Length: 258
Ligand SMILES: Cc1c(C)c2c(c(C)c1O)CC[C@](C)(COc1ccc(C[C@H]3SC(=O)NC3=O)cc1)O2
Ligand SMILES: [Zn+2]
Image 1 (tube, rainbow, N blue to C red):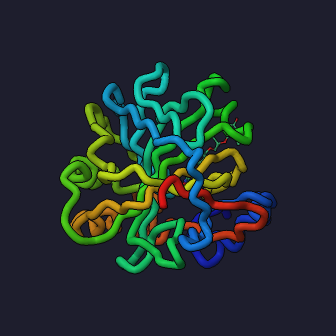
Image 2: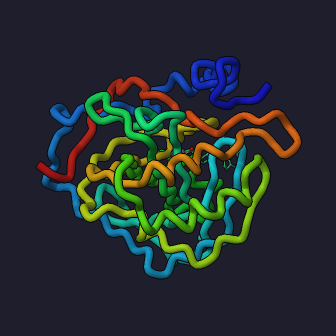
């Protein structure tokens, strides 16, 4: 009986195995656009993905992860609210059963169809496992997806999903360029938070882009054909793999823009 997104093991249950679920800096949150503070001291984000080396795509039973070589400074996030250099290790999505839900963060209580997370770790901690134990260990760049025109840079991801339908399946996934998933603007909100899945560690500086990307209905429909289950288990469609908004508590969301 392990955690997941069902009635019996979903987000409302996670606190029993992971009591920090009720902690002081949990993610995601609702971004109240009118109460976010413009912070003119916030620097532009520096996204350096020109040398990114994708390796593999994995269905881990919760989402699919596109994994990168993080053994060198190849794909790094710097600037914005960050001190030092954060190395890209993986990206994944959260999405809904319907276009009207799927994102983890909300904007004035608006849910997007999906949310992309680009996960980076602070190089001063040496390895991802050490970074997650630190309050400034991770930087996650979150990007909303809305349904409209196709995202050409997403199609290579969509097209490999048939090969990783079930939990524990992986496929080679080299030469994928994550710059093709970015919107035009790097305007962002930022706040201190957590992993949005168990173990829910409070180690993340969240950077959520204001501008969504558009994906086609056909692209997100292919996400919804994935399975939570393993091969030869009863089929459970991988949909609604999002944690709902958690209390903001004693935090202030800062905007990079007016
Ligand atoms: C004891 C121990 C723990 C608890 C440990 C790790 C190691 C090496 C450990 O020895 C590393 C990964 C991990 C198992 C958890 O790391 C994760 C990082 C990110 C995620 C994805 C979350 S965060 C996000 O933006 N959205 C997600 O779904 C899940 C797990 O934590
Ligand atoms: Zn995530």
